[PDB]
Image 1 (cartoon, rainbow over the protein chains, first blue to last red):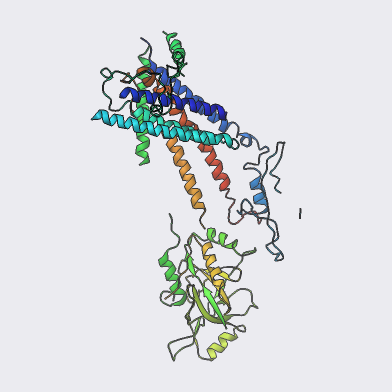
Image 2: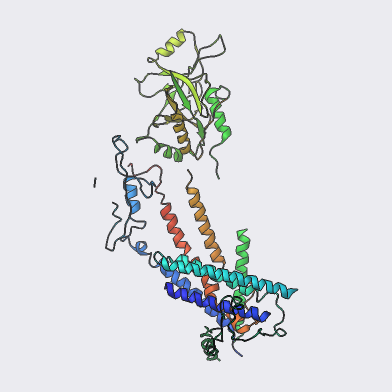
Length: 128
Length: 179
Length: 180
Length: 92
C-alpha cells in the first residue's frame, strides 16, 4: 500500500496547507461527548494491547507447551554445548579443524542457520 | 503586541509544517523506488514523526493564550478567480488559479470528514450522565496518583585491591612482612 | 645469555574459581593441573650486602624430580616502553645435594613458608598463581598472587608485546606492576 | 576490546524506551474534560481531542508494544552466553 499511503499523505498535506493558508489570509442534552470519546479510546487501546498479546504470547508459545521443531532457543545451543564454543568473525563459532593439536594447516567454518518450509527441520549449517 | 507575536508564531509553525510535509513526501517517494525490505517499524516511525510535530504545533497555537472568540470575526481579503502572475507564489500549497465551475465541490476545503454525521446519529440513538462523569473523574485521579507514584519512585564489588597486591609483591621479594 | 619477564599481580580470595575457569581456556590445550611446592630459599652473602638469588623453591611432589634454584636479580636497564625484564639464568641440581653443598660452603636459609597454587601453559610464555600459607617452623598473605613468567634468549624481545596482549585477557581484576 | 558495553547500552536504552512508552499513557492525569472549554471550536477541536487517537494515542502504543519482545530476542541472540567458562559437565 505504498501508493495508497502516499496519496493519503498528499491529501492530508494539501488539506493542512489549504487550512493554514486560509487562516493566514483571514488573519490579515445527554450527549456526553467526552465520555463516549474516552470509552472509544479505552476500547481501542484494549484492542491494540490484545492484538499485541496475541502476536507475542500465542504465536511464540510452541516450545513453551511442548518441545517441537524450532531453531529458536532449542537447536543452536544444543550443537553449541555439544561441539564447540562461541566466536564471532561474522557468525562463525568454533569450527572443527583440529587446531588444538593439528599445527598443519588452518581452516575456518562457514556455519549459519537457514530457513525452509518443512516439518522437523534444524538449522542445517553448511572438503565437503 | 500579542497579536503580532501570535501571527509570527503561526507563520513559523506553518513554515515548519510545510518543511515537515516536504520531508514526509520525499520519504514516501523514496519508499516507492525502494519498495522491497519495507519494515513496518520504519513506516510507523515516519508516520509518528510526521503527525506529532504538526499536531503539537497546531494544538499549541489554538489552546494557549488566545483571546475570546466572540470579538474576532473571520473575513478574507478578496474572492477573485483572477489568474495573476504575481499572486500564484503567495498561497504555498493550493488556490494557485481559481476555476469557474469549482464552487460546488471544492469550496468546503475539500471536505474529507464523513464519520462525524454518522457518530452524531449513533449518539442520538441512545437518547445517567452522572455516574459516568464520576467514574471518569475517579479513573483520572487514579491515573494521576499512579503517575505521581511512578515519578517519585523513579527519582561494583572490587577484587583487585591495590594495597594487598603491592603487599604481596613486596613479600615476594622483600622480607618485611613476609617472614 | 638468557632473560626473563614478569607481569605479576594478585586477586581476591573468593574471586579465584571464576578467574581460573577463564585462565584455563586461554592458551592451554586441556587437562588443568596443580602443584605443591617447597621453599628452600638460602642466603649467600657477608661481604657486599648483595646476596644471590637462592630461592630454591621446588615441588615436594612425587620423588625423582630434582630440587633446584633459579637466577633472578639485578634488574638491568632497557625495556623501552615494556614491562619488567631481567637478564637471568637457571640451574638444576641433584636431589638434596644442592643443600648439602650450600651448607658445606657456609650458607644459611632465608624463608620457611610455602605457597602452593596452580599453573597454566601459555604459548611462548607461562602463567602461575599461588597463595602463602601461615604455618609455624614445624608446620599468611591471604591473597593469591599471580604472575606471567617467560624466559628466553636475547633475540628480539618482541614477544613481550604479545605478553601485553595477555594483559588484555586479564582485564577484570588483574593488572601489571613493578616492585621497588 | 569491550563490545559488551555497546550491548548493555542498547539494552538499557531499549528498557528506558519501554518504560517511557508504558508511562506515556497518562497525559490526561490533570483533567478528564468535564466541561467544554474549547474557545476556538468545540465540534472539530474539543470533541476530536480523543477522536484523533490514531495520531495521538495509537501512534505511540504501536511502537511501544513492539520493542519488548524484539529487544528480548535481540538480547538473547546477540548475547547467547553459552559461557559457563568451565564447561562443567561437558568435560565429564
